[PDB]
Image (spheres, coloured by chain):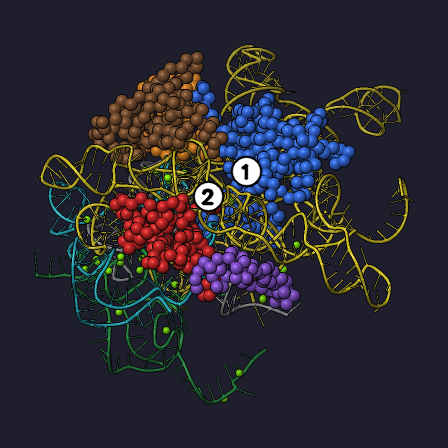
Chain colours: A orange, B red, C blue, D brown, E purple, F green, G cyan, I yellow
Amino acid sequence: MIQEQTMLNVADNSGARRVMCIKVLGGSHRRYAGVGDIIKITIKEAIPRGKVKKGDVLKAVVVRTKKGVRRPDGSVIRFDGNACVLLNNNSEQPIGTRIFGPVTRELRSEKFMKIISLAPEVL
Amino acid sequence: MRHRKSGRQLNRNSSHRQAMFRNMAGSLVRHEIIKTTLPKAKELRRVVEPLITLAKTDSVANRRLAFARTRDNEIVAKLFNELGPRFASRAGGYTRILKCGFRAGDNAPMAYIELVDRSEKAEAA
Amino acid sequence: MIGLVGKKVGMTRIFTEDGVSIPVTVIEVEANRVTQVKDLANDGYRAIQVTTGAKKANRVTKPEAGHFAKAGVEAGRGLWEFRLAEGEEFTVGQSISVELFADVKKVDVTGTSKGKGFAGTVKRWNFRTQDATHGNSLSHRVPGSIGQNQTPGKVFKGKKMAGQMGNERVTVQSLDVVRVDAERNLLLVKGAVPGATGSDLIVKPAVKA
Amino acid sequence: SNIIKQLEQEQMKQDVPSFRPGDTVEVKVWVVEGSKKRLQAFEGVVIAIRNRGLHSAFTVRKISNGEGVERVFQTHSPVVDSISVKRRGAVRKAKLYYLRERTGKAARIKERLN
Amino acid sequence: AVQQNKPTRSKRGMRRSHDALTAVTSLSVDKTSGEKHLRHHITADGYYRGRKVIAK
RNA sequence: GAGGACCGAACCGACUAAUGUUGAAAAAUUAGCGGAUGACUUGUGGCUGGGGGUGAAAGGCCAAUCAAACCGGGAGAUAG
RNA sequence: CAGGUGGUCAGGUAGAGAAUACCAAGGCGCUUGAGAGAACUCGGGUGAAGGAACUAGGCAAAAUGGUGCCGUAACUUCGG
RNA sequence: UUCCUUGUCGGGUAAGUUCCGACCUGCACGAAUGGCGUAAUGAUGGCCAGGCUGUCUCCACCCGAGACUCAGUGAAAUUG
RNA sequence: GAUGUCGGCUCAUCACAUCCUGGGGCUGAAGUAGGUCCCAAGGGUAUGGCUGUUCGCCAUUUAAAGUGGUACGCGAGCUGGGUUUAGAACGUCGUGAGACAGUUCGGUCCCUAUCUGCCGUGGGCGCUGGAGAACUGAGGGGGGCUGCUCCUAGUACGAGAGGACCGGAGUGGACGCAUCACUGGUGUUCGGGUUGUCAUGCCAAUGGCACUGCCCGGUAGCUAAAUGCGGAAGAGAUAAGUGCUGAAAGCAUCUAAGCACGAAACUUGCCCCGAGAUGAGUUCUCCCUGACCCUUUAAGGGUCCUGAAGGAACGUUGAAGACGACGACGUUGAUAGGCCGGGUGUGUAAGCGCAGCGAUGCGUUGAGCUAACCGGUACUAAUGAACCGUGAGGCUUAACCU
Ligand SMILES: [Mg+2]
Ligand SMILES: [Mg+2]
Ligand SMILES: [Mg+2]
Ligand SMILES: [Mg+2]
Ligand SMILES: [Mg+2]
Ligand SMILES: [Mg+2]
Ligand SMILES: [Mg+2]
Ligand SMILES: [Mg+2]
Ligand SMILES: [Mg+2]
Ligand SMILES: [Mg+2]
Ligand SMILES: [Mg+2]
Ligand SMILES: [Mg+2]
Ligand SMILES: [Mg+2]
Ligand SMILES: [Mg+2]
Ligand SMILES: [Mg+2]
Ligand SMILES: [Mg+2]
Ligand SMILES: [Mg+2]
Ligand SMILES: [Mg+2]
Ligand SMILES: [Mg+2]
Ligand SMILES: [Mg+2]
Ligand SMILES: [Mg+2]
Ligand SMILES: [Mg+2]
Ligand SMILES: [Mg+2]
Ligand SMILES: [Mg+2]
Ligand SMILES: [Mg+2]
Ligand SMILES: [Mg+2]
Ligand SMILES: [Mg+2]
Ligand SMILES: [Mg+2]
Ligand SMILES: [Mg+2]
Ligand SMILES: [Mg+2]
Ligand SMILES: [Mg+2]
Ligand SMILES: [Mg+2]
Ligand SMILES: [Mg+2]
Ligand SMILES: [Mg+2]
Ligand SMILES: [Mg+2]
Ligand SMILES: [Mg+2]
Ligand SMILES: [Mg+2]
Ligand SMILES: [Mg+2]
Ligand SMILES: [Mg+2]
Ligand SMILES: [Mg+2]
Ligand SMILES: [Mg+2]
Ligand SMILES: [Mg+2]
Ligand SMILES: [Mg+2]
Ligand SMILES: [Mg+2]
Ligand SMILES: [Mg+2]
């Protein structure tokens, strides 16, 4: 349940540490973005020598939320923080090469198979 | 909305309601019949009758628990020594609400509420 | 096709063996007994009138009792009509069971929604609340403007205002039939249906696809 | 009512083990990835239990790869294959929600030692 | 907000057409004392359904 | 043990908001706010009088009254 | 008539305290009540995820809050 | 204090008619109707950040006082 | 002898000179994508940064971010930033008092709704004997949005790059309705922890007050962020448009006679209201089958007898509700309370024993308590009555029976 102005942690090694969602993509008046949704972000804090720098405007896919995901049997999977993975602004491919922390199977799609294959744990 | 909710507010806050019904329950078991408004009388049933059910099993735990609900040892004594044995065989319904006229000062619907076994032999004590 | 009159028992869930929880509404559908058949000749339209449930003989009036005695059925808790489609034939006194929905896939459930009483415009029409602070004076949940200046000089009919909400007839369409339990007079539909627990429901096959 | 409880008791599992809040359990769930279906384990602390018959549930919390994860299971769902208690904890409360604010040595739970 | 014209005595009487009181339909008669009383209420002397329930 | 020193009650004040606006009140209440040993505050009594007083100065205040108080008189001013 | 009105008296427990909380001595329940438990208004409590995106403006609210010890920058009129 | 004007450049922001730094083209700064600096101070003006939050996305529930019903009393502005 | 004046907020409504979606003609239209014009108003039609701003610029979206009217819609609905009093200052003008759509800081937004209107909800009477139900549907309202992916097909088209129509499937956004099984929120009526203090003689145990004292959990109910469903298909008549046959006019010609297509618009189809539809409809069932007098002799008045069906009232009440209303029930009774059992929540009561110098710990013990929940149970309260409502229901004509 991510909206604009929401700060997210970064679950990859692209160099960013804190990003802020500036737009929930995919529909007019769209309010929230859950796990698996693409968002437009700006980088609020980065490491000194990463692949990205503070101020860039990219896209990201949400991989962990405190609100959590709902499974078809009614189960919930909540996380302690919101996290995303930075994507190329036009190619929608992950920028980093590693993934930290677990992800969910909502990402199990040919578009994010690169993320599923790199994740340390899929829930 | 009020769906399935129980308990009347009686235009009081929670602490006032609790104190009032505590006093009114003590007065009921002391005199075995009192006169009050019909709404107050109907809510008093859900307070005093659980005390009588509690008083059927004499024990220091029940006595203390009854004391916590009434805060009057004279009331607790009568509950466990008189009203307990008197209702040992009755399964609930220890009170009786008899509607009467309207209060002169504010036209409030009044009602008597009494213990059911307040017979002609109650004059002994 | 005709429908049936049941009672909302409540909501539960059905676990599918492949690990899916289906929220279902349990509808008790006892035998619906046909009490009157209307035809084009005598009434100008084809329909059946059914009753269901039971009723204490001391609560039925002589006009109602004579209506049930005319049909030869026991008095139920009410009467409902169903327009007959071309080809459906029913006789008075005939009983209709829940197994009529054996092959029906989707149904429309009609009931009386729960009553909210007098509801404000925020609850009834999803109006936006005005500012809670920033100087707002006694105007937090009020509807705001209700018209234009002198040119119309009136409030248009159908304006959304506060008033009675709920406690009205509501139909939910195209609900999947999860299970038809004939021997227990049960009908499990996926989803939620209008009304409180114990209210009467009218279940008809889906008029749409 | 008698009707609904009759429909629910015929779906409930009959061998769900007894566990309390504070015990560490290992839940094995069914993960379907197409034509396969394997068992994925999920071990952690039971921080809440909802007793509602068929609608009963319990939420397990674990620290996975530095990230805290809570998962609410529907105990009578066929997705949950089995439940095994690893160690029994000794807590005073029924809902261990305060464990969300603690970590490392602060999130330790005494063993019940029964 | 206030009236722009004085309402008439006719309009005033129409509004009060619903203000009429409803007298009690009929009083019950006690089986023992034969007194009249409001139904489901005790009598003036403390009788109800043929029983002296209060001795006052 | 100095201070137009600091924090903060009484006390004096009146910065913000809400309420109230045919008010509980012709200026308040509630929650916060400033000063709080001083150019402080307060009681009692006194003095300054209307083109006059007084004013750390706002044309402020001078009995709910002020770019000239109130009361009586000129006076039935005058009113294209 | 929720305003204003100088001085004197100053118990207990906790507390730095005449703050504050609960009590003593003592005095009161504020001169309409009774029900109900809609919208809406007022005064409050709590709130998933987000956290100023509100708005003229963080208005309001939330938050901070004590004692001891450690530690404390630019700048400085050497006191801060 | 600058009309043209949201001047231009730089900083801050994903985006800054405000803010900070500079430029000088000062419509119409300027030296006791003082010029330029200035630590401390401010219920002073502008701007930023952390924290914090029902300010908001988007409202939900709850506790009280009214509103509503019954009994008693009983106004007001306004009105061809 | 006052029509409150910008912008914002809330809430709108209409126009079409259409921003998107729909239908077309032409193209300097290969395809994709456009350009332009015609038809079309059903629905839809951003969030932010800056500024009082409308606007605009910018950032990032979207199928699209339409243009206008409505006292530049909307202050007896909100706001008060701007403008637009009194204070003060700058620049400027003036000898000066002062002045400046120049600038700057500060600066009281009242009204209990009579009428119309509107949203709800009742009372009366009517509908021609009365009553209880079930309907018909004249008419009215609601609803009508759209993305992306996949298949068709890397096909048609194209040098290549690229890349379809038509048709089908899935899955979203926004919006609406319903619901509470799930996930949660709330839960001052449930349980527990704890600070200060006062009290119950004291210990122990409890209670009061301190915002519910502060907190931690939490039942029912309500509820969204939760999860179900919805927008259609089809039909009729058409718009622009495309035609067939075909003369006037030996040809030609979509038109004059005739015939066929043709869109989210129209009329239906879907949902809701609906016989005060006074044009007051239909169907089924139920109830009433006494006398007598007067008079101006009639749709007359009166007395006695009679009081039905049913209704209302009263009571117990409800997931119904401001009040009315509506629903259930009233001993031939589960309507409410209580009670019994269960469930749920809280988390191992009190007392006692043991260990310890003690705080405390352990055992009895998943104990005790447990609201609104579930299943039972006449223990209490829903009374015999009384009340209202009558006694076969006008005239004319027609078809039928006598
Ligand atoms: Mg009251
Ligand atoms: Mg209701
Ligand atoms: Mg809003
Ligand atoms: Mg005001
Ligand atoms: Mg007109
Ligand atoms: Mg000082
Ligand atoms: Mg001070
Ligand atoms: Mg104050
Ligand atoms: Mg000071
Ligand atoms: Mg002046
Ligand atoms: Mg004065
Ligand atoms: Mg003269
Ligand atoms: Mg004169
Ligand atoms: Mg004083
Ligand atoms: Mg004090
Ligand atoms: Mg209330
Ligand atoms: Mg929150
Ligand atoms: Mg939170
Ligand atoms: Mg934050
Ligand atoms: Mg902003
Ligand atoms: Mg804004
Ligand atoms: Mg503030
Ligand atoms: Mg505060
Ligand atoms: Mg900002
Ligand atoms: Mg700003
Ligand atoms: Mg500058
Ligand atoms: Mg100067
Ligand atoms: Mg100077
Ligand atoms: Mg400053
Ligand atoms: Mg009155
Ligand atoms: Mg006038
Ligand atoms: Mg408009
Ligand atoms: Mg047009
Ligand atoms: Mg249409
Ligand atoms: Mg206007
Ligand atoms: Mg107006
Ligand atoms: Mg202003
Ligand atoms: Mg001035
Ligand atoms: Mg106003
Ligand atoms: Mg009028
Ligand atoms: Mg709940
Ligand atoms: Mg003690
Ligand atoms: Mg006390
Ligand atoms: Mg209290
Ligand atoms: Mg129990």
- Dot 2: within a 10 Å radius of its alpha carbon, few (fewer than 14), some, or many (20 or more) residues? few
Q: Position of residue C105 (x, y in %)?
A: 58, 24
* Frontmost residue, B10 versus I387: I387
Which three-letter amino acid code belongs to the residue tagged 2?
Answer: Arg
Which three-letter amino acid code belongs to the residue tagged 1?
Answer: Ser
Q: Position of residue C178 (x, y in %)?
A: 53, 25
**From where the camera sits, is residue A94 visible?**
no
**From where the camera sits, is residue C57 visible?**
yes
| Left-right relation of C84 to C56 | right
* Frontmost residue, C135 versus F72: C135
| Residue under the image location 70 percent in, 36 percent down | C70
Location of the N terminus of chain A by quadrant is top left
Q: Is residue I209 above or below residue I340?
A: below
Location of the C terminus of chain A by quadrant is top left
- Helix, strand or loop under label 2: loop
Looking at the rendered structure, which numbered label has been put on residue D16? none
- Dot 1: within a 10 Å radius of its alpha carbon, few (fewer than 14), some, or many (20 or more) residues? some
- Label 1, label 2: how far apart the Cα atoms are: 15 Å
| Left-right relation of I328 to I400 | left
| Residue under the image location 49 percent in, 33 percent down | C10
Q: Chain of mark 2?
A: B
Looking at the rendered structure, which numbered label has been put on residue C199? 1
| Residue under the image location 30 percent in, 27 percent down | D19
Choose top left, top right, bottom left or bottom right for residue A56.
top left
Q: Disc 2 marks which residue? A: B4
Q: Chain of mark 1?
A: C
* Frontmost residue, G16 versus F15: G16
